[PDB]
Image (cartoon, rainbow, N blue to C red):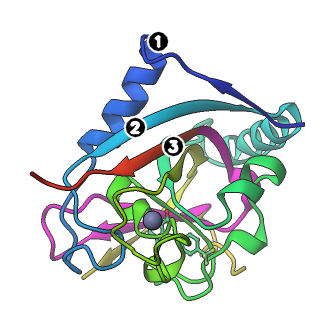
């Protein structure tokens, strides 16, 4: 039931999504090992992901969380990078898209920094890189990220230098804690708490 609608580069929606992607690039402590060396992307396409069933599943859960949290879903728009991007847009998020080894337990991880999510496009630690060139810093192959609507509800704050949410909470917030430049990371434990709204196809660009 999923359809992908292309956004025109002239469309204001295209532009605000591209700005959030571009402006949330930062330097990483691995020096580019996992996600490659770049300061910006070449955006090739942005598509709206439309699936009535997944949307209703998301809104239903959103309403449950909101009613547990003084009518506040604490909804964010966050990046997600995964080798399973193609299953997620068709079937939604679930237990099979969890990161079992994650630092906040086995849940589904999301980032404010687009460049953090870029590190997982080819797998954990960037895996072995693009399938064509086996290169984690490939400047040629097309990459995809999701920009997702995520319900955090009451989020447990972890200061940091499928399982369950900590009791009384709906999510975990990974607060950046030595690297003063890093934005937060977030984890949910129910797939119904995210909807994959935009599919962004891009390349990382080699610095000149
Ligand atoms: C940790 C973390 C922080 C912020 C953003 C992300 C993010 O966007 N993706 C992943 C990610 C990790 C593993 C898998 C896999 F096991 F392959 F299914 C998929 C996605 N981790 C993140
Ligand atoms: Zn490649």
Report whether 1 appears left or right of 49: right
- Judge whether 168 appears above or below 206 on screen: below
Residue occupying image coordinates x 89% and y 37%? 53
Residue 14 drawn at (x, y percent): 45, 22
- Circles 2, 3 touching at the beta carbon (< 8 Å): yes
Q: CA distance from mark 2 to mark 3?
A: 6 Å
Ligand 2: does it lie within 8 Å of the C-beta at label 3? no
Residue occupying image coordinates x 40% and y 69%? 119
**Quadrant housing the N terminus:** top right
- Circles 2, 1 touching at the beta carbon (< 8 Å): no
Write down the quadrant of residue 140 in the picture. Answer: bottom left
Residue 71 drawn at (x, y percent): 62, 35
Residue hosting label 3: 201
Q: CA distance from mark 2 to mark 1?
A: 14 Å
- What are the residue bounds of the magenta stretch? 170-198
Q: Is 189 contained in the magenta span?
A: yes
Residue hosting label 1: 11
Neighbourhood count class around disc 1 (C-alpha, 10 Å): few under 14, some 14–19, many 20 upward: few
Q: Earlier in the sequence, mark 3 or mark 1?
A: 1
Residue hosting label 2: 43
Neighbourhood count class around disc 3 (C-alpha, 10 Å): few under 14, some 14–19, many 20 upward: some
| Local SS, label 2 | strand
Q: Earlier in the sequence, mark 2 or mark 1?
A: 1
| Local SS, label 3 | strand
Q: Earlier in the sequence, mark 2 or mark 3?
A: 2
Residue 110 drawn at (x, y percent): 50, 60
Neighbourhood count class around disc 2 (C-alpha, 10 Å): few under 14, some 14–19, many 20 upward: some
- Judge whether 164 appears above or below 4 on screen: below
């Amino acid at each position: 039931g999923t359809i992908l609608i292309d956004l025109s580069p002239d469309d204001k929606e295209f532009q605000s999504v591209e700005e959030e992607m571009q402006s949330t690039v930062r330097e990483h402590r691995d020096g580019g090992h996992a996600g490659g060396i770049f300061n910006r992307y070449n955006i090739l396409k942005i598509q709206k992901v439309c699936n009535k069933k997944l949307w209703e599943r998301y809104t239903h859960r959103r309403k449950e969380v909101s009613e547990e949290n003084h009518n506040h879903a604490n909804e964010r728009m966050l990046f997600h990078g995964s080798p399973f991007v193609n299953a997620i847009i068709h079937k939604g998020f679930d237990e099979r898209h969890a990161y079992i080894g994650g630092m906040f337990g086995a849940g589904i991880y999301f980032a404010e920094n687009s460049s953090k999510s870029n590190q997982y496009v080819y797998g954990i630690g960037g895996g072995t890189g693009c399938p064509v060139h086996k290169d984690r810093s490939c400047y040629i192959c097309h990459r995809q990220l999701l920009f997702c609507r995520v319900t955090l509800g009451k989020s447990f704050l972890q200061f940091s230098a499928m399982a369950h949410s900590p009791p009384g909470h709906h999510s975990v917030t990974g607060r950046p804690s030595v690297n003063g430049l890093a934005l937060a990371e977030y984890v949910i434990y129910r797939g119904e708490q995210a909807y994959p709204e935009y599919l962004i196809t891009y390349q990382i660009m080699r610095p000149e």
